[PDB]
Image (cartoon, grey):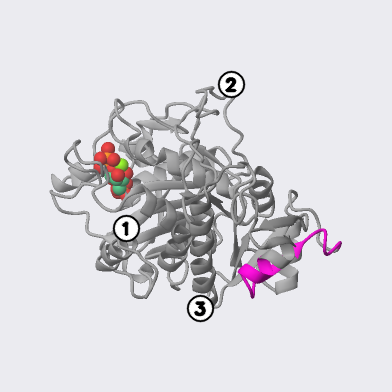
Amino acid sequence: MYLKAVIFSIADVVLPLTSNTQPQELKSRIDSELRKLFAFLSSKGIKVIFLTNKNRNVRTHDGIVTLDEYLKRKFPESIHFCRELDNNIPAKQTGKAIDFIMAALELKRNEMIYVGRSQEDLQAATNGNTLFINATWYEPVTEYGFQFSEPKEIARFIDVFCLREQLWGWQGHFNEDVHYYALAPFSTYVPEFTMYSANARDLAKLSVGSPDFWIRYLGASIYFSGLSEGASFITTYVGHNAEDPYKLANIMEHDLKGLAVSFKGKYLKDLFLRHTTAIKSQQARIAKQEVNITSQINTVNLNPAPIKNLITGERYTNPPKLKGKKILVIDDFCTEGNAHETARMYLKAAGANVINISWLKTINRDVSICEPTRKIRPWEANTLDVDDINYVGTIGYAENVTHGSAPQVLSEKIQQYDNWDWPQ
Ligand SMILES: O=P(O)(O)OC[C@H]1O[C@H](OP(=O)(O)OP(=O)(O)O)[C@H](O)[C@@H]1O
Ligand SMILES: [Mg+2]
């Protein structure tokens, strides 16, 4: 399987620290929900690990016990790594404690995830290149998403996204620097199809799924397939309209920020600029006119001054340093690759290594891999002739659909997720 152990810190996860005043009803409910989570993990053969610095005394309605005895009594069959009890264990903050746990359990790094809340635990997981699961049931977080508001949500995430062999519905490579992934195949070639709700009165603004569903799908599939390893940036593509280019990003920004935090990366919402309104590729296709990649190349470029501080709005003063950096590029659906190949062309010209990820792969359409014959100056507007494109190869649809993947399988995954409850 993919997930073999879950590391839990204690502060504001198993026992509150920040607040004196957590209601007893909350502690009892969290204790009971953690019991369910650990039993669920045990039933799946997933180990439960506690990682702590101090063997502090804990006051019980029965008396005072050490933290080790407390955890052993309430959550038996967990494995407690406590620096005070084992001088072997290196520091948490630097990520070294994760290396130690990996060796002790004979597990690979991305065979574990890390549930925490304290800043030291976020640092421990990210510096240890382990997926961070931000537990916010004792202390809330407002700055970004990809959160987990109660223990049940961790079980939901694991059960829905982390236990099946196929993390991607479609995936393929070309040459050595071209890597394409999509979560699920889907029919996008119908005049009716749109990824965004038709009515602004709906609280759901995506037509398929929801932000919670998609960020958790993305996070699981990217992490357990190894794509997050060494990734510095995550970014989304831009819509065709120069007046409204950030529709997907505006819906998903909150969650993409949190996924970036969990990978020790940065979400660059406006790394791409749509400087001139482009032909809408989907609409050209339904009009049965051919889509040419220069319609994208000639209307987008890399933003030399993206937002560096999504809280403050402060922009980079010099273009972000992308040379030698790994960037995850997200778009909603991929048909023939015009959008992703343009994203890749610009980022590759800036020296980056690129991973092209989509929620959906259009059924029965192959991706054409392109390289420019005119040198791209990626931080400014470029204008290429159709003859400036070298079509070097193909990532086909049919041969790269993964076993068992299908649009109906996505629909049932969404149903499974939306209605999820403790498996009875
Ligand atoms: O793989 P491709 O052949 O590039 O096709 C997929 C692209 O087409 C759609 O955008 P579109 O250009 O229709 O504009 P929109 O997002 O503004 O609706 C979709 O959102 C992708 O960006
Ligand atoms: Mg688009």
* Residue 184 is inside the magenta segment: no
Q: Which residue is mark 2?
A: 317
Q: Earlier in the sequence, mark 3 or mark 1?
A: 3
Q: What's the amino acid at mark 3?
A: Ser
Q: Camera-side residue: 18 or 328?
A: 18
Tag shown at residue 361: 1
Q: In the figure, residue 78 lies in which quadrant?
A: bottom right
Callout 2: CB less than 8 Å from ligand 2? no
Q: Residues within 10 Å of mark 2 (few under 14, many from 20)?
A: few
| Image disc number at residue 91 | none
Q: Residue at x 56, y 61 (%)?
A: 226
Looking at the rendered structure, the secondary structure element under dot 1 is strand
Q: Residues within 10 Å of mark 1 (few under 14, many from 20)?
A: many
Q: Is residue 179 toward the left or the right of residue 289 in the image?
A: right
* Magenta-tinted stretch: 71-87
Q: Residue at x 51, y 78 (%)?
A: 43
Kind of residue at badge 1: Lys
The answer to whether the residue labelled 3 contacts the one labelled 2, judged by CB atoms less than 8 Å apart, is no
Residue 216: in sight, yes or no? yes
Q: What distance separates the C-alpha of mark 3 from that of mark 1? A: 34 Å
The answer to whether residue 225 shows anywhere in this view is no
